[PDB]
Image: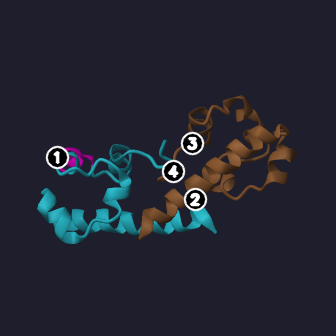
Chain colours: A cyan, B brown
Amino acid sequence: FSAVVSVGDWLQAIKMDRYKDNFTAAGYTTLEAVVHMSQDDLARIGITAITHQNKILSSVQAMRTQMQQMHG
Amino acid sequence: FSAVVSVGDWLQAIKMDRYKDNFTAAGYTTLEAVVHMSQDDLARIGITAITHQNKILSSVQAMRTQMQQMHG
């Protein structure tokens, strides 16, 4: 059991679900793996649009900060 | 948007879903709130069976450790 939601749910929530297959094909099936991605990882995955890279990276930053609060 | 699942999902996963209403009635609607509970909070909520208190507390401990790994 995992306390975190699916990558698919996260992508739809940030309107980047057009990239669902991009994450899956590269083995990024859990948010734990996604949260440790870099800009280069996103480019390698097929997300070359800098705007989309930033939306995803900003979201990752917010999810990490949210997870820090999951254990004060 | 929250990256964590519902209290209901967590309770069913640890077979403590008989207590769904106990959490809700006391305002524990998010896992963020649940993760900061103490034994006394569980008793006050109606979970008096020590075995059930421990199953829940042990789960909380595991979810917290899992969330630490959500930002290495």
Labels 1 and 3 positioned on one and the same chain = no
What is the three-letter code of the residue carrying label 4?
Val
> Are the residues tagged 3 and 2 within 8 Å (C-beta)?
no
Q: Nearer the viewer, residue B13 or B5?
A: B13
Q: What residue did someone put label 1 on?
A: A25
Are marks 2 and 4 in one subunit? yes
Whole-angstrom CA distance, mark 4 to mark 1, is 24 Å
Residue at image position (34%, 50%) is A30
Magenta stretch: helix, strand or loop mostly: helix
Q: Which residues are magenta?
A: A17-22
**Does dot 1 land on a helix, a strand or a loop?**
helix
Q: CA distance from mark 4 to mark 3?
A: 7 Å
SS at circle 4: loop
Q: Nearer the viewer, residue B45 or B64?
A: B64
Name the residue beneath numbered marker 3. Answer: B6
Can residue A2 be found in the magenta stretch?
A: no
Q: Is residue B30 left or right of residue A38?
A: right
Give above or below for A59 relative to B20. below
The structure residue drawn at horizontal position 16% and vertical position 46%, both measured from the top left corner, is A25
Quarter holding residue A52: bottom left
| Residue at horizontal 31 percent and vertical 51 percent from the top | A15
> Marks 2 and 4: which is nearer the front?
2
Q: Residue B1: horizontal and vertical position, in percent?
A: 48, 53
Where is residue A35, by image quadrant?
Answer: bottom left
Question: Which three-letter amino acid code belongs to the residue tagged 1?
Answer: Ala
Q: Mark 4 — on which chain does it sit?
A: B
Where is residue A11 drawn, in percent x and y?
32, 50
Chain hosting mark 3? B
Q: Position of residue B44 (x, y in %)?
A: 87, 46
The local crowd at label 3, few if under 14, some if 14 to 19, many if 20 or more residues have their Cα within 10 Å, is some
Q: Which mark is residue B64?
A: 2
Residue shown at 27% from the left, 65% from the top: A37
